Length: 93
Length: 96
Picture 1: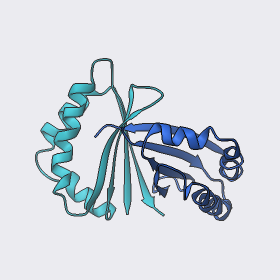
Picture 2: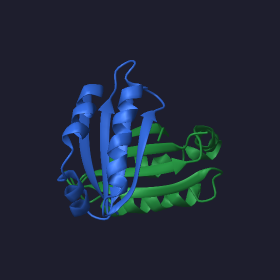
Picture 3: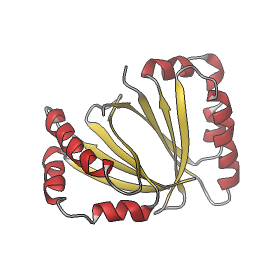
Picture 4: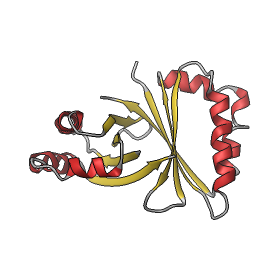
């Protein structure tokens, strides 16, 4: 299994639009072959730091989803609502 | 009301994986019946093999805090502390 950490920074007042951006992504991964779970989280220490994390049957299932059409209006709102974006892949042990 | 997701991002030096995997099991034992503890997961970076992730989910931040603020708990990150060269503990509230 693959666990993705998508770590971002959201600027003041950006919660509403960032959450909407997450929900639109969530819509498309709920239907994705091999999607196991995903969550949107906010740091309890620095409220600017947020996490989108998901779990997949394999890295190949994630890549299939990422390589699907329509992500133009999925990535654009993420860029517009975040000031920093880090992607970290992990294998579940 | 919102669940808490903890990210424990650690680095394990060459030769240390076996003792680290033992430490992960010997913290699962200590939270196995902790009020509000939901689940734990162990992950390893597929980019840098030295980077590992322990992630845990709790019913609420207050549940996790009551388990942490109790006295016999700092003798427990210590096996993780004693098997890793650096550590970063990041707690998150689950928003959706």
